Image 1 (cartoon, rainbow, N blue to C red):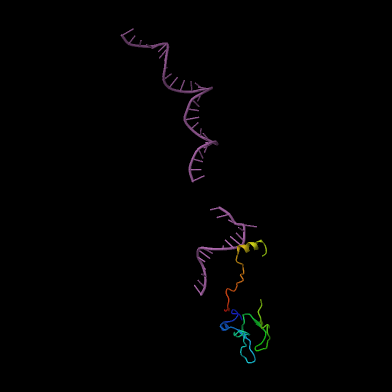
Image 2 (tube, protein in one colour):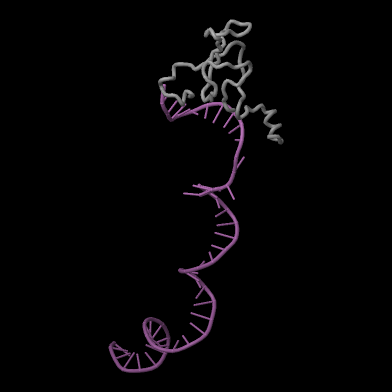
Length: 96
DNA sequence: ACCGCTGCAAGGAATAGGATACTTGCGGGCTATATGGCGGCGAATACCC
């Protein structure tokens, strides 16, 4: 349930999925020391079960997805586009 | 040496005719309340925290 879909109960917690082994502890990302837990976004449809074997690079879950003279005029005039593809302002990790 | 008379002006009724006060349209001279276009953008409010 997205933040909008869910009621007040589940607002605080953040759903996630950590890769684990038979021992139960969190298997680590290769190379680095950040434990591998993937943050499930809202409206994510899941089909697999808990504690079930899966292989590398597999679908853990699914989440669905002018040219005329005015184009030249707009491009030179440097007008802001309708739907700006916001960029990454600086380097580093990101959070909500 | 006095008087009634004739006669010569002043005011009434009928016609023609110009002068002149009155009326009018103008010509120039003057003064002094809408209703089928968008797009961009920036400033100025509105708003609900």
